[PDB]
Image 1: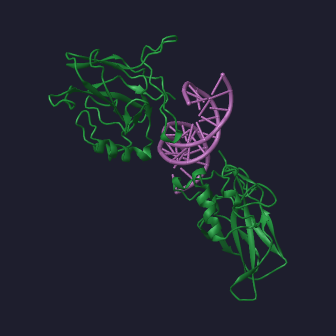
Image 2 (image 1 turned 90 degrees about the vertical axis):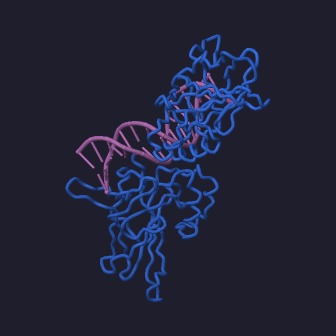
Image 3 (image 1 turned 180 degrees about the horizontal axis):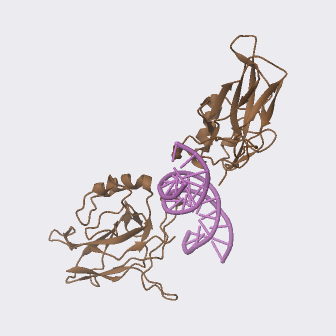
Length: 175
Length: 175
DNA sequence: CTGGGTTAAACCCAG
DNA sequence: CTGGGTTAAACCCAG
């Protein structure tokens, strides 16, 4: 059981918006988004069929041990506290993120933001929040979507078994 | 007794700085500031010789009934609460503002600022603070220096007699 | 409402 | 430290 990123986020097709802009932030197209056929990022679990949720959050482009990136993910579907959580189709085993937007935190706020990511307890690679002290070290123009998948356990209704976090190609703030 | 603006502020020779920039804001040269001979704004009282202080503050470029402009004047000499107060040479009857800088308030702060100008009670033309409600109406790229001169009264040490406020030519934020 | 240019606010480099 | 360009953050126009 592992997750495959079947359609990668287009690396330069969405402007990140600040909270001060009061928008929906939009949606991140897929690499293959086309003229008459729009696309969106999508994953696919392998080796397993059953209940399984997915947590998506921003991690740094930076290092194999990517760290929580301050930026919040907002979206009509499942996004709370910059983290976005949705349940996967229990038979097809795939999900397509059609409303996943990136709301960029500005420098002044990086700390309080990372402060919150910690409360929520979202830390894909067990990186801790050391980077919250050194805020300028974080590149606020690039991120990667992190997909942490959790299989239903044995304790019915409790998604307990975590598959290994999978990181997407880098997404760069478009102008 | 009236005040003459003997050397007018150069209209385009100083960048206004935000409080967030943590500088001295500089000094406003005079219209005639030259290569080997730098100049600065200056006034001259006429019709009177004696004690007399001067209050300088920013008013709008706008209308003969200029209103308190949010921007604060800072300067090594006499500037407190964006308002700057200095005592005039009791014999020559002139003062030359060699350290008068303009610290620009940003939109978010216009209100609280004008709020404060009111507390201080600086309102040259009896305009009230109606403009504090409509903050976008104020052009944050131009100001005029207002020189309110007060003659010593009869109550020794109390500058009581106000001469009529005199307004300087417009000063425009340089890039 | 959305994409995307423009102004404003911050920041920072060179002298 | 200063002048003044540049990035970041806000804002806003056109479609």
